[PDB]
Image 1 (cartoon, each protein chain N blue to C red):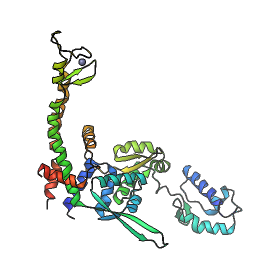
Image 2 (image 1 turned 90 degrees about the horizontal axis):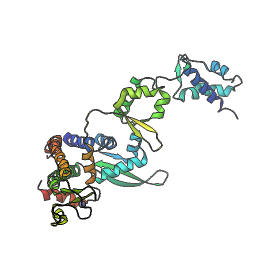
Image 3 (image 1 turned 60 degrees about the vertical axis):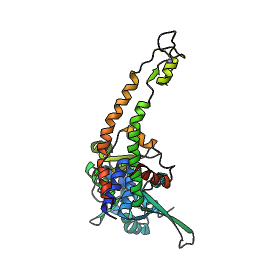
Length: 171
Length: 187
Ligand SMILES: [Zn+2]
């Protein structure tokens, strides 16, 4: 068709160019040259310059030109630790391991380096969710304690019996 | 809402429950009443995961829930689940669990001696002292289980009993901070 597809090639070419290490911004016309979009329509050019290249979260407007956004993406261990801490502080939630691996190349080194600082939750589809390890208050017990705790059923006991136990034992 | 109640709730949730339960309590600590839908978005947890956690929280009655029904702008009925922390019930449940654990410890001490002291390896089943006498045959002159006719060793029963004694001191020591918090929350 028209007016909606040429943008994808621009984004992908921009993504591939960034992977090569070219952080320098690129003009709309310059990017069009290498994407075989010299015949791109005029009303398409303005739409990209006004909406597509600003609304997207991976496009940075620098000195008028447009450049990738590696700063938002995690590309080092420190950002991963800082990013996770911010989510816990603001209660935004965890991030899937896939979102970090794509943003952070060789994320295994960062994950293993931080070690226990990251809490991993395994989704049914094998997907892993990362959460900050809040080391403020920590407490754990032996597996025997947890097994004993589970053996003490509490869901199937009514409030009347629960509170009656308190006076039964004299407390 | 004295800070003592919040501290006690945080200590118990972070000690006897997983991180998921603690995160849910944190939202309710910041705001007394919070919608179930809002909590799901903030935590980004799975719908089933949050529901299972909420049911567990309701099971221990740490936080109560109220159902509000209203008509939305588009006209479709909306039923929201509002969760609020009830410290009055939370302290009672915590007190119930602590005493139940304590009475479990004292009863467990007697349960150790109640365990059978005779075990036949051939049958692989426990044998009581009373049953051991019955199995003994006066004609034979030695005590063996009639079913398998094998010697019985009582050394195995001794080992598990010693383990429980060590747990007594550790359990009492590790639970002191919770007791101190309870005393501070009596007012
Ligand atoms: Zn026997």
